[PDB]
Amino acid sequence: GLDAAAAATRLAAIETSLDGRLGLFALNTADGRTLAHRSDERFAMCSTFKLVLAGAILAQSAQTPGLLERRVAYGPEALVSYSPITQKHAAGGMTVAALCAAAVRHSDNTAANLLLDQLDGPAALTTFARTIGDNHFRLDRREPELNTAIPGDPRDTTTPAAMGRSLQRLALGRALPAEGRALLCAWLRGCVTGAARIRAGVPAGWVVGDKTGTGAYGVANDVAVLWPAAGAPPVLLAIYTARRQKDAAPRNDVIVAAAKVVAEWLGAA
């Protein structure tokens, strides 16, 4: 694969093209090696927090089996922003599992808020992150307010390394029982909001499970498990971007280019 020193120069050049801050952490579980660029700096999570939210709900279900099929009641007054699944189901409600799937696969905002209610709020989700060894994640607000992404504001932020290591524990490790880990990975593989991000920068035969986020200041993020081939050791990849003015455009091309560097570092052509 591409030497880590040359990967570093390529990520720096991609950041120049972004005109902003690129945050990247990759961990190859085959050898335990990493690639890092601003991996210990804070970035606004936007909807990438929903992966940790789904994990927290699965962890709650490990403690109290049956939670996932219990029904949540809500009304249309609770609908916020992009809520494509929850807007269809207010009359009859949705199960906890259906809300998790909507939050991960579709980024459904109201689903995320209803799951935060089930967990007892942003601070409770932050505590869950601390229990899985993440000292950087912090959720402070609910949807749709957590996407302001003001440079330097620590609210609703993480670091790329913290998120990558949390994704490893949740999707590949024992933060959850094997059944719950498997379900989380199934939801991530079913994400339909990230085709133009990490997925577009890796070889055609790789399987991707991801969660996107997008916000003000041109924020465009994608956090993924990469499976190069059936049975091969997976790779964790957390990519965060932030730009320099409030109304900046997101730069998917930067995420794609950074993912391609990671693929080359792993040995892809």
Image: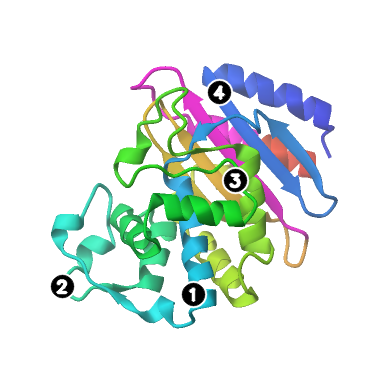
Where is residue 141 shown, x and y percent of the image?
35, 43
Q: Residues within 10 Å of mark 3 (few under 14, many from 20)?
A: many
Q: Reply above or below: 4 against 108.
A: above
Residue shown at 82%/54% (left/top)?
A: 30
Q: Which mark is residue 61?
A: 1
Could you tell me the amino acid type at mark 2?
A: Ala
Q: Give the residue drawn at x 38%, y 22%.
A: 248
Do the numbered discs 2 and 4 sit on residues whose CB atoms are within 8 Å? Answer: no
User: In front here: 185 or 121?
Assistant: 121
**Residue that numbered label 2 is attached to:** 91
Tags 1 and 3 touching, CB below 8 Å? no
How far apart marks 2 and 1 lie (CA) works out to: 25 Å
Q: Which residue is identified by label 4?
A: 21
Q: Is residue 241 magenta?
A: yes
Which one is earlier in the sequence, the residue at label 2 or at label 3? Answer: 2
Question: As shown in the figure, which amino acid type bears the numbered disc 1?
Answer: Ser
Q: CA distance from mark 2 to mark 3?
A: 36 Å
* Secondary-structure class at tag 4: strand
Looking at the rendered image, the quarter that the C terminus falls into is top right
Q: Earlier in the sequence, mark 3 or mark 4?
A: 4
Is 163 left, or right, of 91 in this rendering? Answer: right
What's the distance in space between the residues labelled 1 and 4, CA to CA? Answer: 37 Å
Residue identifier under label 3: 163
| Quadrant showing the N terminus | top right
Q: Which residues are magenta?
A: 233-258
Quadrant hosting residue 118: bottom left
Nearer to us: label 2 or label 3: 3
How far across and how far down the image is residue 178, in percent?
64, 74
Indicate which disc, 1 or 4, sits on the residue closer to the N terminus: 4
